[PDB]
Image (cartoon, rainbow, N blue to C red; front, side, top):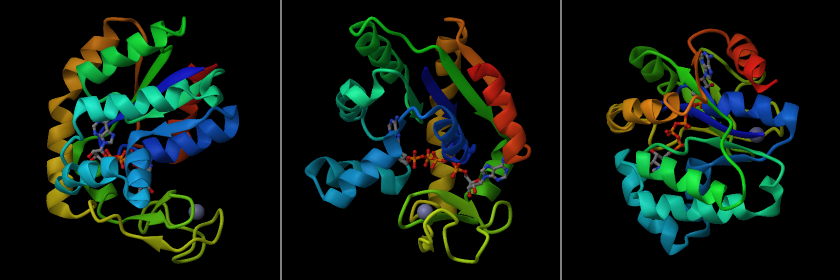
Length: 213
Ligand SMILES: Nc1ncnc2c1ncn2[C@@H]1O[C@H](COP(=O)(O)OP(=O)(O)OP(=O)(O)OP(=O)(O)OP(=O)(O)OC[C@H]2O[C@@H](n3cnc4c(N)ncnc43)[C@H](O)[C@@H]2O)[C@@H](O)[C@H]1O
Ligand SMILES: [Zn+2]
């Protein structure tokens, strides 16, 4: 089960990932989580990634492909994996084909979660993230059971610094700059499915899960 969960910032990739991972027990590999981990280690990689992330810019492709090479070569991905927000560029996409072709494998499904820009913006305005596990809530649209506390581990919730309005606008634009030619890459190789992400979390999930089996 070699999957890519694709979508613009705030499309519900993280939200849908928890469901796919919990159901099929394949590792969730998000580049954005990895960069935040490196920032928490305070590695040099993290310090350098963070300049870009704070602007809402992409982290350079070579850096990014790097950590993905390393990560997907770990034995826990041998039987499958859920890439989340990678690739975002044609060179990332290619380097992914190549590193998998070296292992006698390929990506088998790119699930592209589509949401209009205005909705994406509303989603990243009230978003909250768990200190303990990294899961996201939304104060309006998908709140925790108990205010301020994650439903999974009781973790405190907080606001990601890049979820401010200026950085969000930058993030949507930058990522969209990459999107159509990448859809065209995957659409042409016959693995891309578009998914209406603009409805209930459970309903988006059914659409995904249809494809997964
Ligand atoms: N491959 C790469 N190349 C280069 N640089 C890279 C890279 N990967 C990362 N980077 C760098 O790292 C940075 C951060 O990356 P990262 O943090 O991965 O991602 P992002 O692009 O910032 O967007 P997310 O993946 O955080 O959003 P998502 O769709 O998972 O949203 P969620 O499910 O929370 O949902 C959003 C909100 O909506 C709510 N919600 C979810 N589903 C629904 C629904 N159906 N209806 C209503 N509300 C919903 C949630 O509760 C939540 O509040 C980038 O800006 C870049 O600098
Ligand atoms: Zn949590």
